[PDB]
Image (cartoon, coloured by chain):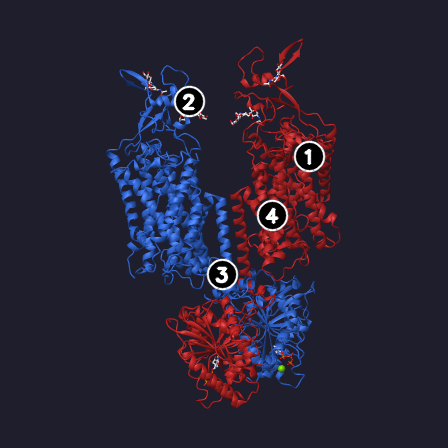
Chain colours: A red, B blue
Amino acid sequence: PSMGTLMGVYLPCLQNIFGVILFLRLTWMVGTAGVLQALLIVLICCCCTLLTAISMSAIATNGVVPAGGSYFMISRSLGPEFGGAVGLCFYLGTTFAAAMYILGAIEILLTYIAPPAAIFYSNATLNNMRVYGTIFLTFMTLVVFVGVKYVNKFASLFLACVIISILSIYAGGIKSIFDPPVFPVCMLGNRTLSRDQFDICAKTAVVDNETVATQLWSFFCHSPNLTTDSCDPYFMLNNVTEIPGIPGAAAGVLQENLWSAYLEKGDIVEKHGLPSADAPSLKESLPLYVVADIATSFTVLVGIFFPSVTGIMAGSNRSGDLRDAQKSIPVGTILAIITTSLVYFSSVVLFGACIEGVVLRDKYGDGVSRNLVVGTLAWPSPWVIVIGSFFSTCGAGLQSLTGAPRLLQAIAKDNIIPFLRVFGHGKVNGEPTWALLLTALIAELGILIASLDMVAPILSMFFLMCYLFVNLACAVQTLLRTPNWRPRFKYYHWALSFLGMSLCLALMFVSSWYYALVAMLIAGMIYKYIEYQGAEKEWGDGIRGLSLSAARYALLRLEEGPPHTKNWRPQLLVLLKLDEDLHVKYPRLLTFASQLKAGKGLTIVGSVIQGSFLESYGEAQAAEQTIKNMMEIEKVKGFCQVVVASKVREGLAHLIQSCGLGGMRHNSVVLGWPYGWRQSEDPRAWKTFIDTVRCTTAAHLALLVPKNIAFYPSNHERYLEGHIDVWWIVHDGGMLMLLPFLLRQHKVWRKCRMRIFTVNSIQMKKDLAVFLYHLRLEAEVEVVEMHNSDISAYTYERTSNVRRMHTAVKLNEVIVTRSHDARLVLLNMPGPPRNSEGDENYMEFLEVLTEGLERVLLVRGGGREVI
Amino acid sequence: PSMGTLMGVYLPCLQNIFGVILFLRLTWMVGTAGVLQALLIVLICCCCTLLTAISMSAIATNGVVPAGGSYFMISRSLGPEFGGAVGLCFYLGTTFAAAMYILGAIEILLTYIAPPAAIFYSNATLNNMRVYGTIFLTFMTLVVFVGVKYVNKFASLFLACVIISILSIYAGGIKSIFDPPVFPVCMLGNRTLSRDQFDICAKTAVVDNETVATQLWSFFCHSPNLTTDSCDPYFMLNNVTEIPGIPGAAAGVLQENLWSAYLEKGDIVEKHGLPSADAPSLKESLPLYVVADIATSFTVLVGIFFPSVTGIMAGSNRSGDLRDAQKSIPVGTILAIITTSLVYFSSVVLFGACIEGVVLRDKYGDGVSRNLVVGTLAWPSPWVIVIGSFFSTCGAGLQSLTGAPRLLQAIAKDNIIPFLRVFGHGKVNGEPTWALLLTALIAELGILIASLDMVAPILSMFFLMCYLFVNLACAVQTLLRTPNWRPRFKYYHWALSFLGMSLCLALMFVSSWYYALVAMLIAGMIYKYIEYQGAEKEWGDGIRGLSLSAARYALLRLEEGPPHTKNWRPQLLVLLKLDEDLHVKYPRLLTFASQLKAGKGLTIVGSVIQGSFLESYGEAQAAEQTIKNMMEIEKVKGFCQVVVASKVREGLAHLIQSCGLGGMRHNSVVLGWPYGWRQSEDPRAWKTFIDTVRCTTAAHLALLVPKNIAFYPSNHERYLEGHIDVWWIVHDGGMLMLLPFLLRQHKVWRKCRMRIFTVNSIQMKKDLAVFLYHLRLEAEVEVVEMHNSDISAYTYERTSNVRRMHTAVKLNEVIVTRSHDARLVLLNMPGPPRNSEGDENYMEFLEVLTEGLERVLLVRGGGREVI
Ligand SMILES: *[C@@H]1O[C@H](CO)[C@@H](O[C@@H]2O[C@H](CO)[C@@H](O[C@@H]3O[C@H](CO)[C@@H](O)[C@H](O)[C@@H]3O)[C@H](O)[C@H]2NC(C)=O)[C@H](O)[C@H]1NC(C)=O
Ligand SMILES: *[C@@H]1O[C@H](CO)[C@@H](O[C@@H]2O[C@H](CO)[C@@H](O[C@@H]3O[C@H](CO)[C@@H](O)[C@H](O)[C@@H]3O)[C@H](O)[C@H]2NC(C)=O)[C@H](O)[C@H]1NC(C)=O
Ligand SMILES: Nc1ncnc2c1ncn2[C@@H]1O[C@H](COP(=O)(O)OP(=O)(O)OP(=O)(O)O)[C@@H](O)[C@H]1O
Ligand SMILES: Nc1ncnc2c1ncn2[C@@H]1O[C@H](COP(=O)(O)OP(=O)(O)OP(=O)(O)O)[C@@H](O)[C@H]1O
Ligand SMILES: *[C@@H]1O[C@H](CO)[C@@H](O[C@@H]2O[C@H](CO)[C@@H](O)[C@H](O)[C@H]2NC(C)=O)[C@H](O)[C@H]1NC(C)=O
Ligand SMILES: *[C@@H]1O[C@H](CO)[C@@H](O[C@@H]2O[C@H](CO)[C@@H](O)[C@H](O)[C@H]2NC(C)=O)[C@H](O)[C@H]1NC(C)=O
Ligand SMILES: [Mg+2]
Ligand SMILES: [Mg+2]
């Protein structure tokens, strides 16, 4: 399968864009709104479609392109929810478009081709439209049922007819510039008379050597004798002129019809710039003037014109039979859009500058003798545009009735929405069976309105909803960094899709707010229903399934990307120690964690249970429930893991290195202090502690070792007088300065004074102060003398056993004489020794250091802390 | 702190609800819209506020009630995002309400109290309103700045004045029924003359024994002599009547003014039911008829009336100083609402049935000699209502200017929105300083409009937005089962909150669609900004923080509730085996998992690395990256865990029992088969396999042991001819029937025929078929003979070593002669023995069973499978 860009993307998109709105409703729109506002309408309606084409190209380039059609790409690149919601709005738009094309062909048949055939001679026109539209819809449905092959064969002919029509229009204009046609329109003062009835527009004619009243007189004056004075004042007071209706292109005409002329329902189409002496008038004369049919505005014209720029999704419709789709879909679509936009602009200016401003406003060509107003300027004859538009409308109706059921069948066989499974019951060949009937029924329900000017806004609403959803999906997926979404289009940026969504939403609300609300509610309902059904199909439950799907999506999206945050906040893993009877030994660790997190962040609570898994599952479940209850009491929102190991050491290690799912990992381990390690003889008291410390420093995790956890305050407790003391010695400054702030952020330490003690002094104070300004703690800074010999233990261990104890006891003396009355004391601990045997000496160091302090918390940095 | 329900909730809510709209704009609304549509407006505007009061009660009962005010409850019970968004709309509503009350007091001062004081004598009224409103706003701001204590002291007086006003109105009506007042209104045909200028309404009066033209003549006719014929035709053609303006209560008047009388801008207030002979008229007479001031409709009246039922959040405003708030806030609020609604209904009917339908439509009381139209019926004098409404408006303005800056200061000190931190810089006493200035500026910007009929819809938009957000939050949090949200209100149901949200949204869009769009965009912007800032504060990054917060919220919400799903879908844990050089040994396990999941669900991929953590972290990270790449290649979306253990057995156990976060856990373990176990001498080949099997059967997890994994198809492979074979023997029927369906759902097995082989036969076939109908697989069912002796191994092991082999070899013979050419064969495996030593015999059994089959997959149920 291989066909080029032109005959694969360009010509189908062109054939789908050029429609009936141009012939039947371009001149009327231009005359009612002027040339300027018409150009503005065309620009506004082309910008939304151009931004949507850019977003569609960004969709069509990422990855491989599915070979099914234009609905499979959207789904594959935006998810079943979005794609399903988009597909239904597009289906409804297409079926209503079929209805509109049938209505247009009926109007062209009953008004210009053969008026005598109308059955009903107000509401007679509406009933004729209803009857003939129903007959046409039935026959077209039968044709599509039996003869799809001939339609696909003859589809080129309709495009040939459209192109020949446009060429003839432009040839007629260019011939108009130097030698225009003749189409006299008659005038009464500054009113417009219907030339259909009268033989000639003249008050009196000379027959048999004398003057006699003409048909215009007998129609306006009921008396057939000139010597009468019982007629309306407007006829006798004003003259009767015959101005040419097609003045050749000039700068005087384009200057005349350049400003808006919005009429009201029932008003008279008047030629601004003719002498008129006002006077009352009878009520038997109104059937002789041309009348405005519907109320005209700006939003009305926007709504009526928009369905003439839709069809940009028809270019990416032979995706399977394409040579290189990534390079052939976007360029073809955008070139088709540009060609259509330039043709519309040129045609607006040409109509404005070539035709009278009073014959453009005859929606049905009443001033002229019931001709196609746009067909008046055409070189060969006004008969080429009539037949051309008739065949174009028939072909567009046939193609819409062919392409809507196929899309419905695709959506039904995709098994997204479950209640429309029957609509996928295709024939033996694949041609839909019970989707054609539903489509014909919806098209009939649309035909029953029987007025293009009322069917067009619904069509516009559905297509605008589809475009808005495509744009919004693209922008959001680009912003939030979805895992499988990376488009390769060059001229693409999420700002463009966002602007397109905004513009098409503005249009959707300008046309009719209530229709837009109904469309938005339908779209939201289908989106949520697709999401719920997908959740129930993946997991098993509806609501819990929704939560599981949201969690999985967030974790998967969070997986990709740089795994480092610009800031550092403690996300703890509280290693609780269960008793022999499975009771929490130190329930104050959970309280302290709740005070340090304040209910925001991640807090996992692990614990190891010695034994064997094969025979100890119930114990694990019971302990998990116990920890969950104890954790609910202390008001800390977190998860709870319980593992059953053979030795507690390896259980602790596995718990430290494996807790979380992907990016939701901990980065801080808060373990308690071993009590009675030197009292008892069992050496294992302090080996587990040292091993967990060494295992949490090799994973680059922070460390919080709250000593004397039995004296820490509870949540009901409150502090009124007291001062936190910080004793940052050398390293770990960031966290030593960030912990007391996050601590005092709690009501228990809501107003505890902070004092920063740091073992040129003025320069150091200035730096600490400038750093504190960003934090805003403003705690008093007191820098005591720094003796390198005393601090040689921290410097030597980071980057002499007898000396170690000396320095630790001198440091302890200083801290206990200058910080004894402190509420909470925070100081950083030195790293454990490299030699696995000096652990006793390291423990003695750590014990003699914090001698006397009532409550002391030791923090060890991980090294990856930034702030 | 303890005060009752009445003086703590009822009276403040009552004082906040009864406003100026009732006096200044009740009669006008009733006359323009009739009695029926007025009652409908009151009902529509009371239903939204009643449903909002029910939702607010449901909020006020769950948990403890914060003692701060009415904004802390909403925040504490709905989250910082919702509460912050609600607080700002409420602040804007309150400040614009202050503007409206100042405008009302100005109107009452310049129109009835003292008209000569107006500075400008159209736009003179607007300029007078602007100047005087600015002066009033300045003086009121200064008073609130200096004298809050006196305001809080005197707040009771304003309620006393309002109550006395209403009592006087009703006393006047009841006195009207039997002896009404005198207020003659003059008429011209069926037009309404302004009685202010004329001395008496009579064409001619008799002075000095003869008739002379009266002031009405000289005002309507410029000639002061009766003998003139140069006047307008309407004056001479019609009469001059003097009808009473206050007809006592009767059923004839309530019948007259019962249908709508919507006028247009500039129309004349006409008395339907008086003789009038039409005629043209001059243009110097229009300043003498009463005129309609603004265009009236239904939506206009809805918008103008709505700010008279707002203030239901003022009852829950002394939460701290309450005896028992859970029982005192809801009953008080709802009783205040009911009292206000009944007073409005009774007043609408009383006005309709007591006053002429032509003097109700004088917005400024022009027909009467510039009196308060509602003050005409009042027993003591019309002077009590004027002064009462003046003092009420002044008091309401003062209280709004006192209560808006306090709310802004609370929001600013809560540190939710960061850019308004300055507005919390209260005085030494707490009274706001730079929040009062901002509030006064916004109120001035609102005063510059200087028309109640244009300020009221903005107020309505803000309050409706606040109410809609409260209702939506309540309904959603009740539906999705938020963890900390359980209200105790009896008459509360999420359907009521949903209906309230719908009704108040309908109102918000009926009044003015564009205003509603602006309000909704403001609310959404503030919601998303609060969410982003909170994410950046909890975690550290903006976008990644958003993802982390969504994941944590979903997991926490999913934690609570029954942990069993009605359906069972496999969520796998693929235990890969890494090589000595850290390469995936069997990369086909990942392919098979991707074919069985099809990219939807949870798939964790664990692996154990022997060694020691203290010295093997880089190996773990490298292996994790390797597995991530290999898993991305095979197109399976899952997480990857790597642990470093000392012995692979306990690593596998810890991986089996601890993988996931809360509810996102696996329920199926897919491990491979040990190859070369009998070939090599190392006994550990089959001990790890048996141990993992026994460890995964004690955790109640399913088990998938794909044998001969080297012959399984790849993703590029396709199958055209072949038939899946199922050999369900006794147990594990649900999963043995669900696995092939989920398998064939993949394109690789898209059309492989399924054959169900099952070792009364007709009854069994009928049951299997009925079960298959729901699945819809419709696979052919062939039931072979079931010999109990051969099946004695499965029956004896679930619920003789020589016999075991016999039965296994006979079963293998049957399966290999009737299923040799099968594509994939699925049969359930028996459980491992209880005796830890018969493992060799169990392995020999499992090996001799699947002898000859090219591809065989064995499944073992967990026992908790439902479908
Ligand atoms: C077509 O002829 C009709 C009827 O002869 C013209 O209607 C009349 O046009 C004159 C302007 O030339 C209007 O006079 C102006 O009226 C406005 C508002 O009343 C006033 O402010 C101006 O100072 C001036 O008096 C006149 O009202 C209008 N007649 C009616 C009944 O409205 C019409 O303008 C002619 N031209 C068109 C339609 O382009
Ligand atoms: C107040 O007096 C005014 C002027 O005298 C009345 O206006 C005129 O009322 C009559 C009805 O009694 C209208 O006649 C009707 O007009 C409609 C539509 O044109 C027609 O369908 C009916 O068959 C009938 O002819 C007349 O049009 C109207 N005059 C104008 C200029 O509109 C008015 O109705 C009196 N009563 C009120 C306002 O309650
Ligand atoms: N079985 C366990 N499960 C979870 N965490 C543990 C376990 N054992 C120890 N820990 C962690 O190590 C810390 C040190 O406890 P450790 O057992 O060393 O001291 P102890 O229990 O107070 O008594 P001793 O020091 O005499 O053994 C505990 O607070 C806990 O954080
Ligand atoms: N180190 C490991 N990490 C993760 N999973 C493992 C590990 N070792 C074994 N397993 C699991 O157990 C299964 C059995 O593998 P096992 O080592 O028993 O057989 P083998 O490697 O094929 O060779 P042999 O049977 O001779 O040892 C593996 O497929 C895997 O699922
Ligand atoms: C009606 O048509 C006539 C014919 O063109 C207009 O012109 C008038 O012709 C008479 C004949 O001599 C002259 O006396 C008048 O002076 C002409 N009018 C002007 C303005 O020159 C006539 O004006 C038309 N009437 C109206 C109301 O347009
Ligand atoms: C104007 O007022 C008079 C006084 O009430 C109306 O009544 C007419 O009075 C004259 C005096 O004899 C009678 O002849 C007429 O028959 C009375 N009218 C009727 C209907 O009985 C008079 O009708 C008023 N005019 C209008 C237009 O309402
Ligand atoms: Mg120990
Ligand atoms: Mg082994």
Quadrant of image for the N terminus of chain B? bottom left
Gap between marks 3 and 4 measured at Cα: 30 Å
Q: Position of residue A584 (x, y in %)?
A: 43, 78
Q: Secondary structure at mark 3?
A: helix
In front: label 2 or label 4: 2
Residues B196 and A80: in front is B196
**Disc assigned to residue B278:** 2
Image quadrant of ligand 8? bottom right
Gap between marks 4 and 1 measured at Cα: 35 Å
**Disc assigned to residue A543:** 3
Q: On the rendered structure, is B181 left or right of A744? A: left
Q: Is residue B825 above or below residue A581?
A: above
In front: label 3 or label 2: 2
* Amino acid type, mark 3: Ile
| Label 4 sits on residue | A91
Q: Mark 4 or mark 1: which comes first in sequence?
A: 4
Q: Position of residue A839 (x, y in %)?
A: 52, 87
